[PDB]
Length: 205
Image (cartoon, rainbow, N blue to C red):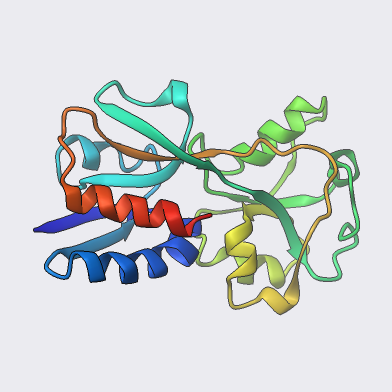
């Protein structure tokens, strides 16, 4: 009667608090253990049963065979800088090509989202200003610098420095990651876990 799971920052900030409230009404007897986790770091923990499931970005084709992937949603990735950044009003990635970036976490390694974005539009590599694996730390770091970064729209909307940040109004396309429910496919689902996932799905809409 316990559920142990990991959640992405976007989910942890909006869907999760509402989902745990609704879930606790329906299953008042189940104790939840929630933690951060991103793929591929969660993979060993999913494999060995220490996590029941992880809600995380990943890429369909790049997930260990042991795991199934129920896609929930495509995240909304935004580019974020300090509010009066010289590139605040930029609409094309080429206009950003000389900025320094805070490379943020992603399944394929820090900055993978912006590097992939720059690559797909025929640009050279984005310039590395620093690596910030902590989504907790990221908004305050960017607010106190002229670094740009990428983050989930949910983090951009819900962080303690929101009054000191902007989102770049891009007309170019960012490779949005798909958020999955990741879990051993040989693990039957309990109605408790399944219901918690439905609630998270419901409130992330």
